[PDB]
Image (tube, rainbow over all chains, first blue to last red; front, side):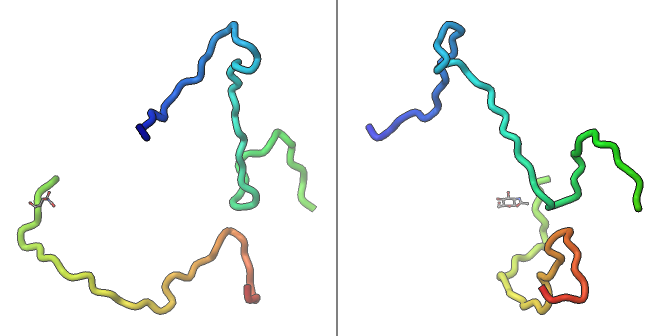
Length: 49
Length: 36
Ligand SMILES: *[C@@H]1O[C@H](CO)[C@@H](O)[C@H](O)[C@H]1NC(C)=O
């Protein structure tokens, strides 16, 4: 009474419908202008004028 | 490791005031000759 076990598991079966099909979710997070950016795409740098 | 110092003596939590302490550059953004 007034006591529940919070830890639970997601039921995963390959025959379940699309509602129960697990989707791996990778949330992409970033910081803007808070530091020099060390991650930048392969965009070739140019000369300075 | 867990060995206590013998001659060590406790002291009450005395307090001390600071003057300019706590002032720093907020971040990598630079400013000069201005008041922000
Ligand atoms: C020192 O002695 C106290 C009281 O017996 C003990 O709780 C503690 O674990 C010992 N070790 C240190 C260095 O605090």
